[PDB]
Amino acid sequence: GAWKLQTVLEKVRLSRHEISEAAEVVNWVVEHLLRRLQGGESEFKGVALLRTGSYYERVKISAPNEFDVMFKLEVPRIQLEEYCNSGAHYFVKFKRNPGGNPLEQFLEKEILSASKMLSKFRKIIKEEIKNIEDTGVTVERKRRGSPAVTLLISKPKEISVDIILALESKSSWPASTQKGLPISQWLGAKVKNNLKRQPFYLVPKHAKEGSGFQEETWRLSFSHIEKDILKNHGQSKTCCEIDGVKCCRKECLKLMKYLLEQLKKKFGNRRELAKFCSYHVKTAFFHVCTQDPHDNQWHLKNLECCFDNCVAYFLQCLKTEQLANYFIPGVNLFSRDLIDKPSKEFLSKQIEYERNNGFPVFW
Ligand SMILES: O=c1ccn([C@@H]2O[C@H](COP(=O)(O)OP(=O)(O)OP(=O)(O)O)[C@@H](O)[C@H]2O)c(=O)[nH]1
Ligand SMILES: [Mg+2]
Ligand SMILES: [Zn+2]
Image (tube, rainbow, N blue to C red; front, side):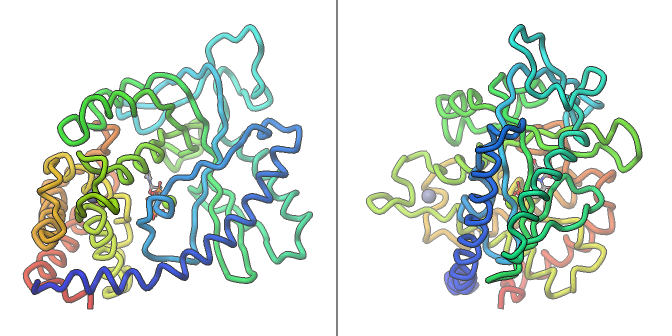
């Protein structure tokens, strides 16, 4: 193959060891923290580690010094109120409970308060980290527009860990997701039904930068579903297994992430590139899996054409300024409210240039 994509995949593979070692350090610290939370008497006594995200999907290809971790908390009887038109943001309310509400301390005027819950969450984390301060682990100061409590691990490696609190609701998916997860052709109706019977999650997200009740909103998270469709990505159950056939679906996702990350290193993460992240290419990739549902379309030998399909689709989204959230179709990740036109223009041009020259940024 002229692009020599197998050699590129070998290069990104080199990063694997560093990422696995760092992940062990992160897991040690977070397991300590979890055991403290679970042995305590706080509302967060029921938290558990939610093993999702790029690391557990095995597509974390970079940034061994940066991890995010999700703590899930089962919350019964949730009732959502949409913040606005989109389904991007919700207020969390509760349905009547004759047995009570363990989260009463966080209620403010009908609504579960995110700032109240996070303050208490941050407080508990800070006290547990202070208790083990000889370990060299500290809590980073609050960042603007970040729902996370960031841990700074200094030894034996410098690692930033974003701890994200996620509410778990074992209830029907909200109406905004009705035409979401369009995987029927790709994975089948049975798989789609099974996945939509899983719980959904809520993580704190500000609706707009203002000061006000937009500070109290939550966004949906389906990171556990994303993990499953990445891991069990074939029409056949033996796709990419030892006794099955190798497809190149994951390799393509990795190359798309790597493309964006190498462009940022090439250009110095300038203003135009700073708003694009791996979640945009992951979303584009899922839409491509839907348009090309068959395992034989992704046979390993077909790597160049498959990767080119992903790139071409991503180019089409940049030009049309349309990239629908895979679970919430009414949410456009490429709207002008989020990313201005010249930024899309600049990335389009660079991707077009890379494509026409065999992706020299990879080398
Ligand atoms: O539904 C989503 C999910 C994720 N995101 C955004 O994408 C970013 C990463 O989101 P994720 O943490 O959930 O995806 P990821 O593991 O696969 O990506 P990386 O960690 O490698 O970066 C987060 O900073 C979040 O703000 C959304 O905006 N919406
Ligand atoms: Mg992540
Ligand atoms: Zn496969």
